[PDB]
Length: 6
Length: 216
Length: 216
Image 1 (cartoon, rainbow over the protein chains, first blue to last red):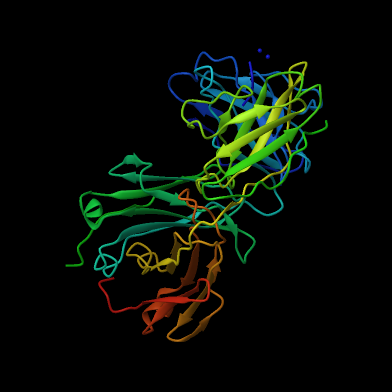
Image 2: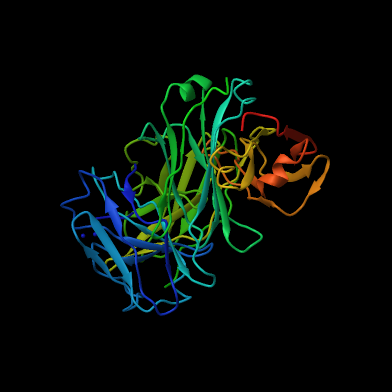
């Protein structure tokens, strides 16, 4: 899991 | 952190499409138009297959499809491949950081028939309770595809307190074996009406229940 | 798609320090302060330990620490625990919504102590015998290192067939848990004197015995 829509 | 609960094994023959459904928990995992999805292969690096509910990445096929119900986010692989074989995981966030991950799902291309676990539950011995130890074993045998989700009860109320479980190992007969335990005090045992062991495979869930007896 | 370059091992000692490096391009590990680090064990549900170049989640103290230089990121995990035995994958943002990941990894945490096993051997249950079947679990608990050689016997002369011994896997106390089943028919059980489990851990046998003449 990620960063951000960004 | 913790809770996103998907299927243990999701199986499929080469062609025959497969869906991986991931359910969430009561707050965070509701009015949430995120949820990404990952694939993790043999030894290799994880890849992003779906991002934010339904969209895809650059090098990703026309094959893969993620969706909404409310609680559940699906992933329908349409056109199954040997290339598609892998472990797969569903995501999310909360806090800013506090981002929850799925319990994992095998995707299997069937090369052997489907078997549903012969789930034998044992109590602690006359002797083991002479020893001032208490441990129960849930032996899970003779299954294919080879991903089981296990869960213990104490008086029907679900334990995550004393439990160690093993990764599923291939037997002599090409099917699989696993094993879970619960360790207590000889009084922690005696104090209850019943204990149980519940196992999720494909279609199946299967319980088995032991009550404390004296042998005296 | 092209992946980020890491070392495949990052060995430290129990309370030392370790640098895992992850290296990319000016398009990824260099363009954006959007590099993430992930902790994953042996088949398990897979956690995120640091989220936005340097900043940590909800509880991971100030010992899981990270840094960027230019084209290289680095995770300087301080004061080794034993728990941390894991595959540490990095990531970073490519642009145009997609995310790029690190190579197939592993930290070996050196100088942890050696556990000689708890061997718990069971009877067949009064569920099983009533089913006209008999099976006995030899549980091999909380041992380090993850090498054991299990062997069984009938009264004193070996059983090789009936037996199905599982592989080594981590307890989340980060030692090992493994099992072995010997599947009989209750006539073959009730005939004998002894039915033993003999397990070889690091140049020592641990034989337990189980017998008939009991309450079952």
